[PDB]
Image: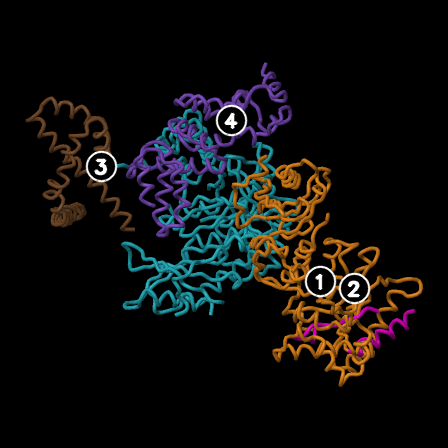
Chain colours: A purple, B cyan, C orange, D brown
Amino acid sequence: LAQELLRKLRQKQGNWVEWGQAIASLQKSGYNPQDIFEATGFEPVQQNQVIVGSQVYNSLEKSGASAATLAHYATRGSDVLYELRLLTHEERAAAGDLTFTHKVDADEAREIAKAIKDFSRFRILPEGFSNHPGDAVAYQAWKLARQYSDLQERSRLIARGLRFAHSETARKQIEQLL
Amino acid sequence: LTYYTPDYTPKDTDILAAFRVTPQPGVPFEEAAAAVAAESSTRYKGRCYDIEPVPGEDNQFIAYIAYPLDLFEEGSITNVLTSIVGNVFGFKALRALRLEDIRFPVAYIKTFQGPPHGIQVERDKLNKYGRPLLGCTISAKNYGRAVYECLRGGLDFTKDDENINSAPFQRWRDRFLFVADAITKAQAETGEIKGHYLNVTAPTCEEMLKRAEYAKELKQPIIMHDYLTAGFTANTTLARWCRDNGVLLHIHNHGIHFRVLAKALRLSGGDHIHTGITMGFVDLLRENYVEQDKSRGIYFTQDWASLPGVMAVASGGIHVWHMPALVEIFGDDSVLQAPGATANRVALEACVQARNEGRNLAREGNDVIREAAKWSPELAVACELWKEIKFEFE
Amino acid sequence: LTYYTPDYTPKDTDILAAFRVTPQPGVPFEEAAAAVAAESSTRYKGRCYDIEPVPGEDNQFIAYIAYPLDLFEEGSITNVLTSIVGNVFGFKALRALRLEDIRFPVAYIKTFQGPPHGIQVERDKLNKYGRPLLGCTISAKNYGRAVYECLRGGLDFTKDDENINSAPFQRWRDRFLFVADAITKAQAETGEIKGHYLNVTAPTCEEMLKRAEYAKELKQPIIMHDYLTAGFTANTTLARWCRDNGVLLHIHNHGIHFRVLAKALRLSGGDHIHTGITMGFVDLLRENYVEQDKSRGIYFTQDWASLPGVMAVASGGIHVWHMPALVEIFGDDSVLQAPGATANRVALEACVQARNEGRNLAREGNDVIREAAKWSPELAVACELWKEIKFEFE
Amino acid sequence: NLKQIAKDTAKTLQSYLTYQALMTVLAQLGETNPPLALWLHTFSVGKVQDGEAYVKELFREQPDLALRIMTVREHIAEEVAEFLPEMVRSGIQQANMEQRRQHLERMTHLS
């Protein structure tokens, strides 16, 4: 009797991971996605963001995140957690905490998930940085700020460089720019 | 020597070029760059404002030339590519010369209309969402019978490539029907909508206007041709046949680098073009804003300022077993190239769910191909055909 | 209240408005401005970033609202004037509301094509260079006989103004010939080329397409109509009849100030429009760059970035004796309104040479009119008719 | 090209030179500290390639013996790796003499 997962959607019953998981039930019982929108108000383009989000949020509380991150990402903050899809199971919950505090938008957490991707693509840690994503986006913001030889152009990358840098050794590398 | 003023900041609205220059023996680095910015154009003159060198390579230096805004015609790629590098490749005082980059302003990008269809607009008639595409290259009836059985394995389209025009054994009209009659017998029998990409190349353009009005009468999907042996002038009479019809989007030491050729081709038009630096222009066709990465060939900074993206085509060859290596690098928004066609769709669809679990698809790619053999006999054959060649010589 | 973020600098590419607001009693200055920036539009929202007051006037404050770039359609004045002030004039929480200014970006100005003809392009068929122009307003034969003798005194054109359409006493066709037959008899007999500006106003536009194809067949000069009882939509079907023909350029407490209406009308089109603040928009129609003059109504800064200028029309009335007062203020590049017509050309042509000697034409203006009476009998009559009214009561 | 080759060759033989590093330590600790050789032999079997990125995993659990492996990259990589030039091309000429002979072995079989 899978029709009671048809009912909990046009009544607005639950929160967004509760719909993010009830879709993948119905996507394992022979459903064409095209006809899912006929009885429930979500086209599978819009369902696509909460499939992958609940495929992240089951990994967010798994990998040891804090309480307030697991409180607000139960209710709001949807498409940011769609953008952490290109990571692994081990570093998403480290970034779910970090992209909550700064209240970043869709496109900014797009590139933070890109910056932690290349910082973890490396076989080697670069100088003065650790495993935290606050060091990841402050490594790129310093690696791409060495190339300016001008003072009043690099502080666009130093204010953001002093916005994320997590350990104190990663704070000194930003301080050499000044 | 008023063509070299390094005491100058290039404005917010200037057009702005680079050049990886290599001069003859004894030729200084400061007069070869004034030999470029002056002989391009003729307050109406370009000025080489910077002279940065290149470390550990054959005597190159990076010349930053800044042309004004008004020097050029609004909405033209032929003008920009010709008033800049007209007779500048023709000097003997240089050993080589390449054109690595161009910054268009925000003010000049939005004169152009761009690609007709984007990362959003492509999914309307194309029934594929959130997963990349597939398509393989192919008398007259027997030619129609072969595409009749390639699309029946998972190929999202096929390719009438390798230059099949109307020869005396296989005319142009009797090839269109038999690969239109071969779509109507695979649309319903496979549950999806597929095209067969067909050449429109003719001697004239009046004949080319008949090889594209016959194709889509209301008959037929989105059907393309090239840019070589053709121009940004030849493919403007038919890329703007997509301004009525939505029908042609695939474009199939001493030079001009491809990322200049890719700025010229988004702004001209088309929805997915064929091709750190491999990652470089594929973050120009797809992104909105790109900050300056000198180790990627991206020497400038220009936001694209709300204009439709364009995807990429796989350009390495046959790839049947080397499937998860492409899925990470080109991402979601790209396009890739009947038992031999059913092995292609299965290896593509499998990896995408093992990415979304959180499994590191870079360090695990082959085992995802191996677990997909236990329900697919066409991947049982292919993995043995490809290469396991290694070295453990430590 | 996310529609008021004063912690924000408006970007290089934002669209940027002002408003001279006046609220009801007790209504704060910070919520009336969020009552404007929010109910205009609906990252896609305008934000009032500044709240500056007005000294010594009835409780006004200047609201600086910043809409994004992408919010609007490229090349449209109807959209910009409607998505901004659609239902914002319809509140009861304000006593008044005016729209004093708009900054268009550099990126959005050069989407538009602008006036077809400028301060340069007007001098091609118009045979007048470096000196302003002259033109006076006028059965069917007897109407043709009167313009037959106004242009024969120096009038560079004439005006079929005060709304003469086809009435049952004077039809539309039998007015065009008799003021075309009256140009062919004054072009050669006076040594210059003159037009007679004629109305094209019809009920339909299919009839208006016949009142403008008959006028210039190849018959006739540059011939205009209005903007009121008409739109930026009505005069787009015929201002782009100047994109083939070069033929229609003259445009003849609680509101919208004229300098908003003048940005809307250069960018739409036309070569000389009818109208510190009188000096204000006439340094917007004619200039390239204008820096912020808060005591002139020019509250913003935007370079026009290479787009054709547009001149001004004298708007005070009959001016026969008050000639050198207009020549300084509107300058060279403007337009002004048979014995009674020969007094007009003489008083204009005389002052211009006494400016170029170096004589201060402001503090000397009447004596230049008086010395031009000793070779012209038509200026002997006019200076006695006008006003010498003074007060020496010290 | 060749710089694609030569930079790939630079890391391969390096990882081979960091193996003779680990083997010199291996015979050394079979004489000084036989408990330390029996535990180094336990970690050695783990099938981990990339000798440069193999010593980094040694610093994770044992930051000290990974310096003695590194020590001979200055000391034993000078008596092994600078003798490579005069000792490749001699073997190339030998393979030009070992293998040209069997073109004659088929020819005598064809004789």
CA gap between label 1 and label 3 equals 78 Å
Quarter of the figure with residue C315: bottom right
Which chain letter goes with mark 4? A
CA gap between label 1 and label 2 equals 20 Å
Considering depth in this image, is A81 or C121 the residue closer to the camera? Answer: C121
Q: Which residue is mark 3?
A: D52
Nearer to us of marks 2 and 3 is 2
Task: Identify the magenta region.
Answer: C126-153
Same-chain status of marks 3 and 4:
no
Q: Which residue is mark 1?
A: C273
Identified by mark 4, the residue type is Ile
CA gap between label 4 and label 1 equals 60 Å
CA gap between label 2 and label 3 equals 84 Å
Q: Is residue C232 magenta?
A: no
Identified by mark 2, the residue type is Ala
Farthest left residue in view: D31
CA gap between label 2 and label 4 equals 63 Å
Identified by mark 3, the residue type is Glu
Same-chain status of marks 2 and 4:
no
CA gap between label 3 and label 4 equals 41 Å
Considering depth in this image, is D68 or B231 the residue closer to the camera? Answer: D68
Q: Which residue is mark 4?
A: A51
| Residue A55 location (% of width, % of height) | 47, 25
Considering depth in this image, is B326 or A67 the residue closer to the camera? Answer: A67
The residue lying at 35 percent from left, 33 percent from top is: A166
Q: Which residue is mark 2?
A: C212
| Residue A159 location (% of width, % of height) | 41, 41
